[PDB]
Image: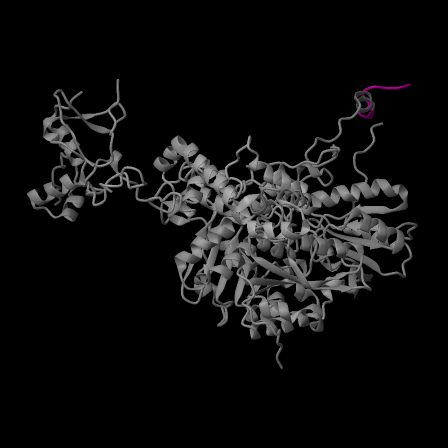
Amino acid sequence: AEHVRAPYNGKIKFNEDLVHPTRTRHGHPAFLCYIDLSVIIES
Amino acid sequence: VPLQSPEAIEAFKMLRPSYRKKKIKEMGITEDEWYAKQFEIRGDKPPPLDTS
Amino acid sequence: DKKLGRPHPFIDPTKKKQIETTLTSDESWWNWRKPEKEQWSRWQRRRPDVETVFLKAMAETGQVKLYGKEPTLTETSLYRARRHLFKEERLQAERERLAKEGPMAFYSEWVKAWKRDTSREAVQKHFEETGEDENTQLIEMFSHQTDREYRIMMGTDVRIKRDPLAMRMKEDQIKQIWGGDPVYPTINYIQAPDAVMDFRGPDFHEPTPNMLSYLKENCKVISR
Amino acid sequence: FVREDYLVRKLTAEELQELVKGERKVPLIVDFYATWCGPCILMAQELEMLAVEYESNAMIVKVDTDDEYEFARDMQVRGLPTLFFISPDPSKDAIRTEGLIPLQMMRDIIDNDM
Amino acid sequence: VDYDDGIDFPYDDPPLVCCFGAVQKEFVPVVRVHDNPMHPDIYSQWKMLQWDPPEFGRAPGGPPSNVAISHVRLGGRAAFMGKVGGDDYGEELVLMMNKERVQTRGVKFDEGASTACTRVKIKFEDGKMKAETVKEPPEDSLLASELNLAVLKEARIFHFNSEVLTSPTMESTLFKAIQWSKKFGGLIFFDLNLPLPLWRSRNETRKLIKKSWDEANIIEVSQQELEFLLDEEYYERRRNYTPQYFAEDFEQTKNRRDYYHYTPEEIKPLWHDDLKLLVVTDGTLRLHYYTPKFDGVVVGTEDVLITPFTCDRTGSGDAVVAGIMRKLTTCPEMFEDQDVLERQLRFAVAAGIISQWTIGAVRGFPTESATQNLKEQVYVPSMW
């Protein structure tokens, strides 16, 4: 799997209601998405 | 898996203390009363003593 | 900035940039919280680089200006990309100082024993009596140069072209290349040449006995 | 036979009273080491070298102040590494030295003061 | 009565410290009985007693010359004030001082005595062997007329240790030096480093050191020295106590070493009006500090098993004292700001730690740069 990494410092912004809650392979909570999601980074 | 159980989604939301704060304000129970109430016996309280 | 951000040094992001406020602790999942005490890490301490000492020395000489008192890793990466430009600029300023001052005044930096006036005017006014032209005066000045001073001057050799700044950084600055004295003291490693090992010293095993001597001593083997 | 690795001889305080009361032909060097003490690793090697160099011409012995602490205090020892040089002539005052003195100072004392 | 140097320039930037007393190449005054001997003859095993050491010996102090060397190497300036013999060994000790750039203008040079050599008469009493000093060594016999008053004028801290109290002459000279230093506005540092004779009984040592202790403005005592000047047995019972049924907190379950922080009320029998700072040292592991206004504890550390073959505890307490003086002279907010005091005492901790990693004391005192490096590597940046 490829990792998407923040290209800039800033504030992440997205509507987290569009995405399903999940537990990651590492036990971390995460969102699992099955759409094209646009994430803002307010740098 | 993307979590499906309402109770597991609720636990996922409770992972933020701010959401717990909002649940406190919505239910109206004071937050120390809720910290107490989390210690409540989980169920099946025994039949009351009838001592004569 | 908007003008003169071409050529000269300028802040990479334009001034008046906006800032943002984000999730405080207790608004965040446990895996995305800053710990309530700053954790120890072996990597906690800025790595000392050649590029940091040189970029600080350029900042203090005013050849460059920096956003803060310490060169960021971005700035040191750019220095890594561009240092030869500043080196050749310093070497050119050194050639031009040679041309202005003349060889007596230039090379007298490495002849502490030469106390006489070295300015071109004084070289002329000395030629006007002692008959020694500028060259004979320069030969005499170098005749007062000590071997150690000459070896230091050899940085100015036209083939070496040692950086005028690297020739003049002082010890307490050069120290910052590796990051000061080693924490474990090097005297623990220093050993003299022609030192002979004391095998009776406190970091050797007790001398192994001769196997026959040991067996005899333990009355395991007999002689007669 | 296998020859013993160490010449400096450990004594009890009573064996030392015996050795000081009895008549001596040679200077007696008493080392008040203790086994936890850092400088005593070095002093023990200096004294081993002295004990070889003088052969039978000096009696070099040591007293562990873990065992004979009150005797060390009565000897007016105020630290370790400390050393007494006791003359074979019983009229002379003994010399106490303190710290890692050079092995050449030990030789000086033994040859010229004892 | 007054003394004038005839000079008005502001001396020099790192303020001078004067270290008064004796010089020895290396020498441990603090000796007590220890439970574990290693083999009596094999010195190849005494490393095991420098990495799991007696608690009184966890960070030995030494001669004040060790503190002078360490303080100069930590970047300060030290003068050593004392006396040596005219013999080769007194020259060797002065050369050691000079090569370490310790200023030796107060070092006198007796010509008729033999440096380390003390004359003693061996005697028998109660059937036990005893000694009595027939002649004191040079370093014990500095006179009050041999003090260098230019040093005491310049010196901002006058450091001494209790070994000088084992000589009546040196004790009288010490108190004259203290009077002079206090007249010139100096601070009196009293590194206790109790020698063997002063471990005989609490209530004799307490009166022996009383005048010195009450003259000191700053005091260094090991944990073991403080507990010996207080009730040694009470603090033994304090730390050998374990709850019979359950612990009173979770941490008491962990059975970790007892870093007990003496309260100001327990220190009160020793506290006095001139005392600006008392430091109780539990190795480099902790420095407790007490002032008229606040008390606390700098948590330190040690490692020594990092260098099992080359480690040696000797001089770690001298390097701690030298680091304390090094910061006291250049950051006197140590007496007034608690965070500053802690942050600066962590430098003394780091100096002690580095001093534990080589054989020999003078061989091992760290530089300022190495000490600051170790501070910044051990401690989190928040607490540099």
Q: Residue at x 7, y 46 (%)?
A: B28
C219 in magenta: yes
Residue E328 at x, y percent in the picture: 50, 60
Residue E198, horizontal then vertical, whole percent: 64, 62
Q: Is residue C213 left or right of residue C173?
A: right
Name the magenta segment's main secondary structure.
Answer: loop
Q: Nearer the viewer, residue D5 or E346?
A: E346
Q: Quadrant of the C terminus of chain D?
A: bottom right
Q: Residue at x 65, y 53 (%)?
A: E31
Q: Residue E274 at x, y = what percent?
A: 50, 71
Q: Is residue C208 above or below residue E169?
A: above
Q: Is residue E43 left or right of residue E280?
A: right
Residue D23 percent coordinates (x, y): 91, 53
Please identify the quarter of the rendering in which residue E53 is found: top right
Q: Is residue C198 left or right of residue D37?
A: right
For residue C20, above or below residue E10: above
Q: Quadrant of the N terminus of chain D?
A: top right
Q: State how many labels appear.
A: 0
Is residue C165 visible from the viewing direction of this image?
no
Residue at left 86%, top 41%?
D53
Front one among E364 and E162? E364
When asked about the image quadrant of residue D50, the answer is top right
The residue range painted magenta reads: C217-224
| Residue C188 among magenta residues | no
